Image 1: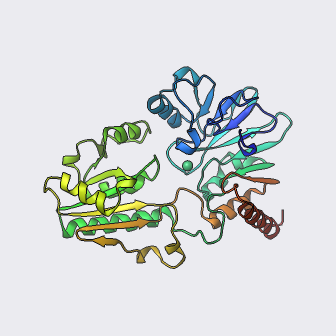
Image 2: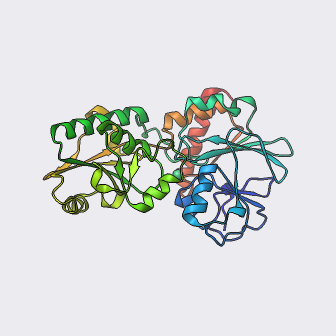
Amino acid sequence: TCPFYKKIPGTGFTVDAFQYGVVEGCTAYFLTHFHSDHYAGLSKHFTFPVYCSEITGNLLKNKLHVQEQYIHPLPLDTECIVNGVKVVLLDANHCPGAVMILFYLPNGTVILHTGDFRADPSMERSLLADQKVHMLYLDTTYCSPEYTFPSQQEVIRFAINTAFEAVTLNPHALVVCGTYSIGKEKVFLAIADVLGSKVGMSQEKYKTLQCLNIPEINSLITTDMCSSLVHLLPMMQINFKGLQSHLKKCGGKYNQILAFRPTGWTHSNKFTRIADVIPQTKGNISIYGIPYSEHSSYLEMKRFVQWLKPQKIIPTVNVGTWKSRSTMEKYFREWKLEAGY
Ligand code: NI
């Protein structure tokens, strides 16, 4: 049955609630972004109205074969009317096409649902600045003070520098980047850009990327693996056995693999600066875990909430244990006390 934190009170709306069958009372289904824990249940047989961004709509049509008459894409940063209720979609700084959703209830209540987001001060100058928010449905994925991580820009600098140095020293090295969903595209694209290569990948992953409006993408990606020195592979293949096998498949074109596994967080962040990160090596294979996050750090999340000053916070992540819920509620109280709302 649909959990309560996926239901918008005073409307016929749900958010990311497609794995429950027909939700009793539901007149429109919102989808924040194209990741499988959120879309699980959409297909060509779905015949309710789905509201989402343009890019998420492109992916629904092409990857899942949802029929076009049921897809209702909305422009960002624009007041739109859905079943008599004013709504606005805002950039969530998560993966391509990911949004937050502002709802303006008929009774005057204002609700923000973050979806998955990485808070940023640029958000403090969107249509959020212009009115009060009564309820916040918050992506709390890393709501504990141990979760620190660097900016995306510092992680990309590290990756570009590492790869440019390895290939300059050995022009027969192959660079590999792991992936399992959309998101984190800047990793493999920035590396390709510095080496003056295109990124080679499967036809299916190429198709996915062509759905994302990314300008000059024909210029950065390809399915001709042979002409590329940056290959994208399944995340499950980013291990010593998997990359040994891939290297054999390259026909003696390359004699060394440098691989990157972007990840959310790892405990090494508690002890280690980005500059100090080192690979796991075996034979002619090195694997770098890099802390490229598309969710808020604890301190980014705290700043956002203390800026917004909501009257009630409803967590959407880590809600399944009493100890987690308790812990998050204690931080919310502190934030409120410290900020004086
Ligand atoms: Ni996500």
